[PDB]
Image: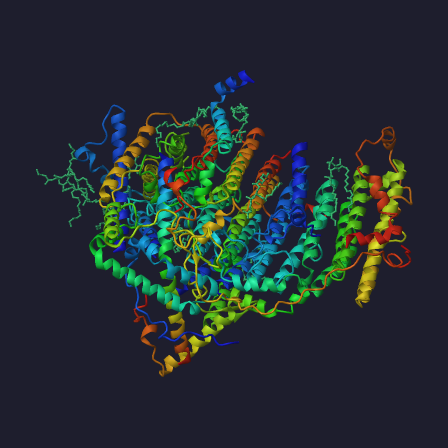
Amino acid sequence: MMTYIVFILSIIFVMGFVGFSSKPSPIYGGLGLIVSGGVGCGIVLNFGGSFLGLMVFLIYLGGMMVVFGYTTAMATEQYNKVVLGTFITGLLMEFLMVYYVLKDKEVEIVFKFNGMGDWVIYDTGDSGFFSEEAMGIAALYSYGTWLVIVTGWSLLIGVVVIMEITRGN
Amino acid sequence: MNPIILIIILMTVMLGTIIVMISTHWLLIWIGFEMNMLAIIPIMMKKHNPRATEASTKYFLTQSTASMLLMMAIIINLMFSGQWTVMKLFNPMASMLMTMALAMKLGMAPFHFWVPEVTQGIPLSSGLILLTWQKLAPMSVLYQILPSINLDLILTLSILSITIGGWGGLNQTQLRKIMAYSSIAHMGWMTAVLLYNPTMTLLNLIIYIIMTSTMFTLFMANSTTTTLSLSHTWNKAPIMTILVLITLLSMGGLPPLSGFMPKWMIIQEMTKNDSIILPTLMAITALLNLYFYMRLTYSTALTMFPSTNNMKMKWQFPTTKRMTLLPTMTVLSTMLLPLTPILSILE
Amino acid sequence: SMMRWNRERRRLQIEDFEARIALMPLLQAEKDRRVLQMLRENLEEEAT
Amino acid sequence: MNLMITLLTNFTLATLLVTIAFWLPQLNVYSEKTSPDPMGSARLPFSMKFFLVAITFLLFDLEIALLLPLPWASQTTNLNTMLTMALLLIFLLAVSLAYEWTQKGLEWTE
Amino acid sequence: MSLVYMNIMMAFTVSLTGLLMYRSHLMSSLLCLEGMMLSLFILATLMILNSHFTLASMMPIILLVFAACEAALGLSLLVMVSNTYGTDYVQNLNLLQC
Amino acid sequence: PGIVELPSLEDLKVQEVKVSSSVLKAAAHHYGAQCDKPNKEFMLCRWEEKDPRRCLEEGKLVNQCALEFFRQIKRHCAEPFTEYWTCIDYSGLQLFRRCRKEQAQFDKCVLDKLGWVRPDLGELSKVTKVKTDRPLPENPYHSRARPEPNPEVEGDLKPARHGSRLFFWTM
Amino acid sequence: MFMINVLTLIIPILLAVAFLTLVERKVLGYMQFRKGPNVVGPYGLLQPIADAIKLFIKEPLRPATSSISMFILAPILALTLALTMWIPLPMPYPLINMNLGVLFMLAMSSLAVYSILWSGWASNSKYALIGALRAVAQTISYEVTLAIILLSVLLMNGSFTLSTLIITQEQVWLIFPAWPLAMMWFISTLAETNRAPFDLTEGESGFNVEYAAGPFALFFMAEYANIIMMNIFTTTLFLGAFHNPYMPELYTINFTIKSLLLSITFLWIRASYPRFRYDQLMHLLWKNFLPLTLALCMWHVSLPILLSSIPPQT
Amino acid sequence: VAAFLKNVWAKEPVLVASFAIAGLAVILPTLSPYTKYSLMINRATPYNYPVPLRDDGNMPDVPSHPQDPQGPSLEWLKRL
Amino acid sequence: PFFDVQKKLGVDLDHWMTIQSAEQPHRIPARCHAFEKEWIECAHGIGSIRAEKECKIEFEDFRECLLRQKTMKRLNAIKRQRDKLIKEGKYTPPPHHSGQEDLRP
Ligand SMILES: CCCCCCCCCCCCCCCCCC(=O)OC[C@H](COP(=O)([O-])OCC[N+](C)(C)C)OC(=O)CCCCCCCCCCCCCCCCC
Ligand SMILES: CCCCCCCCCCCCCCCCCC(=O)OC[C@H](COP(=O)(O)OCCN)OC(=O)CCCCCCCCCCCCCCCCC
Ligand SMILES: CCCCCCCCCCCCCCCCCC(=O)OC[C@H](COP(=O)(O)OCCN)OC(=O)CCCCCCCCCCCCCCCCC
Ligand SMILES: CCCCCCCCCCCCCCCCCC(=O)OC[C@H](COP(=O)(O)OCCN)OC(=O)CCCCCCCCCCCCCCCCC
Ligand SMILES: CCCCCCCCCCCCCCCCCC(=O)OC[C@H](COP(=O)(O)OCCN)OC(=O)CCCCCCCCCCCCCCCCC
Ligand SMILES: CCCCCCCCCCCCCCCCCC(=O)OC[C@H](COP(=O)(O)OCCN)OC(=O)CCCCCCCCCCCCCCCCC
Ligand SMILES: CCCCCCCCCCC1=C(C)C(=O)C(OC)=C(OC)C1=O
């Protein structure tokens, strides 16, 4: 069962998505999204992407969901059947999908998926004296000149836009 | 709003459209789309009233949903092809998701519900910017991926857009909602002729852009947003009544005006591929667009509605608005049929 | 001080990398023989 | 492997300490209290200043995410291009800060 | 293909159906939208890392940056409508029916 | 499709260099200096053929040369090399700068016993040239025949016959 | 065997926190011309034990919380994130050797504000919520300068690994080439852990006014663990010690002395100056610290290129 | 132009220091003679294998052994 | 419209990312470099209509490298037959497949 760790983490990810997507309350949705983001970062880390998972923790959770919950605290003043119904039925489709995957080791819904453990797709070689994802990200200042330019311009324009529309005049 | 900040934001909108047009990478297409939408949001909220914020909220939600669907299609295509070159797609699911994302961005039916409300809630100049410039990039992306487009899906979207646009515009009295439903019908025509000859789509896009620009420019020149306020124009400037009469006749596709040429060439192209029922149905449906255009011309130019007393006070002053390019697009939208073979420059 | 110590560290890194470069042909040969043995054993058990 | 063992140990030690801190005076039977903020029932006033500083933090955090791979990126051969792109990114950070400064964005929470 | 791909597609579909059916609040719609982006992040990152596409490793960072700027714009719009009406309910954004 | 061909288990049989990583790292520079020719021949065969089954014999020769290198080390300089790889093996990152004294002792011993000189900086990272007798693989990717290209444009451009030929237009 | 390492990491943290309370009381007393506790034990050595037992037999407040879930969860997160920010610290060998330990620490520090947010929202008091929102805004606004300063300092290191930070300072201390970054980093870490002259929640409602005495003690213990951790991180960054690979006790004693001196400097700071206003510290950050941090970041990007002193990647 | 600098250095010294440091950082790497050393130090670091070339017969520059005189040299790095 | 500004101007704004078999930093190869190279050397210069039919086997090999459905299916069938034979009791696993091999290097 330890070879299925990424699969189990993906199950927790989709279960948290069902939980927060039922919309019980905006703050509880934010809490469920935080938990789901943590589990997804765990998936990425177990796949080998340390830098991208730590970006998820630093920017998505520590930097942006803070803003979401901060805005949620400035509205939605503090103190159902639908929420419980959709949570129950989403859990039902999820566990039915898991049972159909693991019983026959193959499934088709829109694409064809295989029920074996996901350690099979990994590469048998070593990367030498560097990590491949860090070199790929580090090539942004040497190769991605145009990407840097358009992203920075969009960020500055976003600052200008937010300052423009919240003024009220 | 600062003039310099307005200039920077408008060049950011055009920069996003250019980035979509010139790039060979799917991520750059996505980046250009978000840059364009983020920059165009403050143009909608120039006046700061609750209607503008409501329209901006609905526009933001629709464009964000369409953008997420587009990214989903791109990621599926990368998964099934291993590359990002903007060309034909290698998965029917990716093609369907991208086609519906571009349909949501264009506002074609049944994703049309945001267009009239958004056009109504924003000023005339921002509505002109939206309905004219915002549609250059999704049609370019559609122009790049036609080997992967499902024919049944795009033809269903086209006929649904034409019928829903005509039936929707039959009931409106506000000018911006009429322009929105007219836009929906014209995008139905454009994506109807897309898979047979995209040059006809480019020609229809250019002609619709010119006609819409002329009509919106006349609207802001006279500062009219309703039917009756437009009907007051005969007692202020009758030359504008003549101009709106000829432009609305040309918008209905009546020969020998320049609006006849797009549907004429579209019907010419569709019959070469042994499709006869659809061009007849689209012409019969475009008769409804002609109907509410003719109702507008009745209320404005061919009759004299009663005016009020203060029109004399308005007589004593001349206009000073910068009606930019208004005679040029007025001429180019009515007397361009003898230059029909000029469409070969677009191939 | 940082300039002198970082230049020395760069020289040490170059020495370490060139030691690895001298080593790794033998590791490449061993890895190739090992993966060929694994494939042969799996093929024989698949035949069984 | 060892990392998630340590994470589980820290989580279970924290939840053990919190459980003992909660439920130990629960075993006491002290009393029952009726108890019948300076504002009584006033609505929370919506302030644009706190939202503005939150959004400014978010945007600067995004440009920080862009700036993060500089120690790895300094090892490239194309040093002139990397230096120019790094200086351009931090210059855009400074320009956004200056635009917030001049248009009274940092006002009454300076 | 693999299994975690199926789970991430189903997570994206769940977040999409959550966004496409509003309950009461606009904030829940924004949360569903950002969960959709997070699922896109995980899917693209797993595909790029498994395919050993080195130069594509910069894409999820740009995706995160652009969609978080999108979310900042959406939060500003939500704050504006909350200042207008006193709450962020989606039933108060119905003036443009007429 | 086809049946993948694998060498028999007797063809993969060779006696191994059964030494640890720090033992390899201590004499790495001298191994690169002394046993360079069969290593570079094997690497050229590997990067050219793109198939380990075509480089099995070169790898076997690499093993033989490395084994003889370590036998020659053992004959004369067993004790200083043993101390050197011991103090290399103590370190967590296996640093070369924590064992300079024993390195100098081993280098001096092997210089006066075997005449070996360690390479300087950048020498082992050079690109060398290899004289081999095996022929170059003319088609190493096993690619099949490429599709024939379309015929291109030839001839001068002439005006259109009777213009556009679009309905009634005579131009 | 590894659980022994985990336990001997995490139990001395709590012991050092309790004796940090005692040391701060005694040092503030001797700095205010008086004595600290010296009656409960010999020189007050039994004061934390008595105070802990008293706080753990105190009556709970039993509030009318809006959500008991996050009311439980906020001290859980505070204590877990206080204890989990010690595992990549080299002492001189980290318990969990991380390739990206510095950025892992940044992620945990950025994640630490949810305890403040949930403690503010769980309490029914609106003034408590307002105080929590102000504290969260100050915390994230100083996260910004923490990130820029750490990024600019790391350009002399060459990687995000915390163990290489000892190797970099093998020649000279890193406070010599980066002392303005050291001063700004020290003030930013002082304002990061909500300490004087930035502890606005004690000046005129805290974010945990409705919390019981036990959970309040847990929050305060997490804050003190954060203080010790930040001072150890600052010592590793700027005041690196001599590490003999055969005698690790030399490095352990050296950085222990330096980090204790830095924490005593924290207590020395807290009893010298008046508190800031909210807008005054926002002015100090957005208009004083941030432009100089950006200028020094550009300087420390462009400097190792012009000096031919790029640190090695590995 | 001259009294403006004195006034702005008496009034906002933090911004003067920030702008001066920024100007130094942006004009000094184009002026220093050690940038080329950084370039050829970064490009002389051996990350991957130096794959040998098949000897056709005409390569006098390419060495047949690492200790051969021909080839790139790092004596400039050893001295500096 | 697809205005090829990059080819007209000679700039390279996004072609470096556009394929996986392109110039990658530190000469790092991808998992399916060879298959993608063969497919591109097919499809170049013949249009999409001819390349969708002429050497489709290169694209099938590329897709099999990318997603590996056939290899997964073959491994599933082999393991299923092994499980059936193990449960029915007519197959004994070898020592080297049970962790008692003492691997080569
Ligand atoms: C870790 C090592 C130890 C660190 C220090 C620990 C002990 C010292 C503790 C001090 C007291 C701490 C408590 C109070 C904290 C809050 C107050 C505070 O810090 O305010 C900061 C104050 C705030 O400034 P301010 O508010 O006074 O500024 C006035 C601004 N107006 C007019 C708009 C109101 O100063 C700074 O922010 C400066 C930061 C450090 C600057 C370093 C510059 C280095 C030199 C650059 C070059 C200069 C020459 C010119 C250019 C040459 C180019 C070649
Ligand atoms: C294959 C095709 C590829 C692409 C080919 C090229 C396509 C071109 C598309 C043009 C799109 C035009 C978009 C709308 C105008 C943009 C400029 C703008 O911002 O105008 C609005 C602006 C607002 O200013 P304000 O003063 O607030 O106005 C309110 C009234 N007082 O200012 C005003 O309101 C001033 C009043 C006059 C405005 C006149 C604008 C005319 C623009 C259209 C010209 C004709 C179309 C272009 C040429 C033909 C292209 C096919
Ligand atoms: C990493 C290191 C951490 C160290 C943490 C602790 C630091 C401080 C250590 C202790 C310092 C000295 C404390 C002395 C306490 C008083 C001892 C004493 O004499 O108590 C007498 C009292 C009454 O006695 P009685 O018999 O009534 O007298 C009549 C006779 N004429 O009798 C009583 O009160 C009853 C008996 C009390 C005995 C108390 C003994 C000390 C308890 C210390 C607790 C912590 C110990 C260390 C734990 C961590 C290390 C293992
Ligand atoms: C089954 C049998 C066991 C049952 C459970 C009991 C466990 C042991 C509990 C502690 C020992 C019991 C006796 C407690 C003290 C009683 C005697 C007393 O009152 O001594 C007073 C004396 C100081 O005299 P004082 O009145 O303060 O005079 C001031 C100076 N003029 O005081 C002193 O000199 C110091 C007294 C120190 C008391 C012991 C040390 C503290 C408690 C340590 C253990 C519990 C806490 C462990 C750590 C928890 C985490 C912080
Ligand atoms: C309200 C809910 C409860 C709240 C309290 C509890 C949760 C919050 C507090 C704890 C936070 C834990 C964060 C864990 C991830 C941190 C990043 C990380 O693991 O970095 C270390 C390392 C990457 O570094 P590197 O050196 O590259 O790896 C070794 C390379 N040779 O990576 C590795 O070594 C990878 C090891 C395998 C993968 C580990 C996956 C861990 C489990 C998933 C996440 C768990 C937390 C989920 C909840 C988040 C918050 C809600
Ligand atoms: C070109 C170099 C590189 C540039 C890019 C990198 C920049 C790094 C630093 C980023 C700083 C970002 C924020 C800048 C804000 C400047 C505008 C400003 O604050 O103006 C207002 C201020 C007067 O203050 P006040 O209006 O009262 O505001 C309340 C605070 N007292 O006004 C002032 O105090 C006057 C500020 C303007 C004049 C400053 C002159 C400094 C000259 C230093 C020596 C020359 C350095 C070389 C560069 C050329 C500079 C012109
Ligand atoms: C495992 C539990 C260990 C004991 C709990 C932490 C140590 C006790 C702290 C008590 C305390 C002391 C001494 C204290 O002096 C103090 O004043 C600043 C507090 O805050 C009001 C305290 O909470």
Say which residue appears at 47% left-offset and 32% top-offset.
Answer: H32
Task: Please state which of residues E84 and C27 is positioned toward the viewer in this rendering.
Answer: C27
Percent coordinates x, y for residue B186 in the rendering: 77, 54
Left or right position of D36 against F144: left
Left or right: where B256 falls relative to A27: right
Q: Nearer the viewer, residue G32 or G72?
A: G32
Query: Where residue F157 sits: x, y (%)?
Result: 81, 56
Say whether residue F59 is left or right of residue F159: left
Q: Along the line of sight, which residue is nearer the eye, E97 or F67? A: F67
Q: Residue furthest top?
A: H3
Can the viewer see residue C17?
A: yes
Q: Quadrant of residue B150?
A: bottom right
Q: Is residue A88 above or below residue E86?
A: below
F45 versus G187 height, above or below: below
User: In the depicted view, which residue is nearer to us: H14 or G246?
Assistant: G246
Counting from the top left corner in percent of width and height, residue B121 is at: 70, 43
Q: How many marks?
A: 0
Residue at 65% from the left image edge and 38% from the top image edge:
B9
- Image height check: is F106 above or below G236? below
